[PDB]
Image (cartoon, helix red, strand yellow):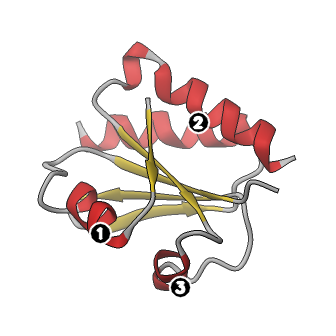
Amino acid sequence: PVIEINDQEQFTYLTTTAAGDKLIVLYFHTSWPCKALKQVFEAISNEPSNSNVSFLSIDADENSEISELFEISAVPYFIIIHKGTILKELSGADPKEYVSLLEDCKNSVN
């Protein structure tokens, strides 16, 4: 599953206080093409073998401060975070590239 991010305190809680040592995957998007890709992101998030990864979707227009923090200039955009730092950023567009990277990262951090 995905958690929809709607405010800064929630975002901070889920990426820090409540994050443990999980891989955290951020998906920046807009609700106005980008809709279809969010559905794929959600489906990937719903895989049982991803049950130990935290997936956070972030509407870039509704979450200005978070977009600024990550210097988002285009969507869709992926940021993978682990143990308090950014592990990888990826110019969001291609599900195959995304799954490939996610599986490598999951393996690297295990």
Pair 1/3: label in front:
3
Q: CA distance from mark 1 to mark 2?
A: 20 Å
Tag 3 residue: 68
Farthest residue, direction right: 33
Q: Earlier in the sequence, mark 1 or mark 2?
A: 1
Q: CA distance from mark 2 to mark 3?
A: 27 Å
Q: Earlier in the sequence, mark 2 or mark 3?
A: 3
Q: Position of residue 87 (x, y in %)?
A: 39, 62
The vertical placement of 14 against 43, above or below, is below
Residue 100 got which mark? 2
In the image, what residue occupies the spot 74% across and 72% down? 74
Q: Position of residue 50 (x, y in %)?
A: 39, 25
Q: Earlier in the sequence, mark 1 or mark 3?
A: 3
- Foreground pick, 53 / 67: 67
Tag 1 residue: 85
- Badge 3, how many Cα within 10 Å: few under 14, some, many 20+? few
Of the residues shown, which amino acid type is indicated by label 2?
A: Ser
Rendered-image quadrant of the C terminus:
top left
> Horizontally, is 73 left or right of 17 in the view?
right
